[PDB]
Length: 103
Image 1 (cartoon, helix red, strand yellow):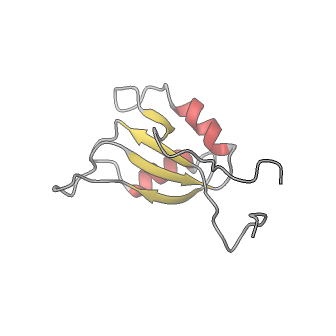
Image 2: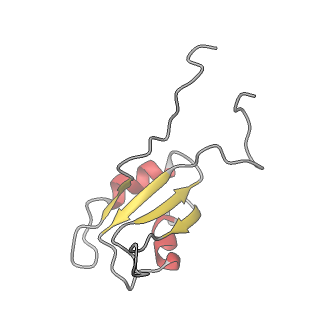
């Protein structure tokens, strides 16, 4: 099969990483931070290997590949919580995959 549909399936939605997030932060808030531009498919906040606490960065899924790009630049580089929140895409895990180049 060759990917070419949408709806009842998720190929690989865009993922945005948000660092400099204080404990006070929660799925709701983090969800309202992006929801402003583009709804959030899912919200996850990794924790310490031992302690169940937001290590430091969070994961936010999006629907389109545009909204995310906007919130990324817009947010990243703003004055929040008395600091410069790092709202950008994850470090690793490319959103693309090798395969049929021409087909």
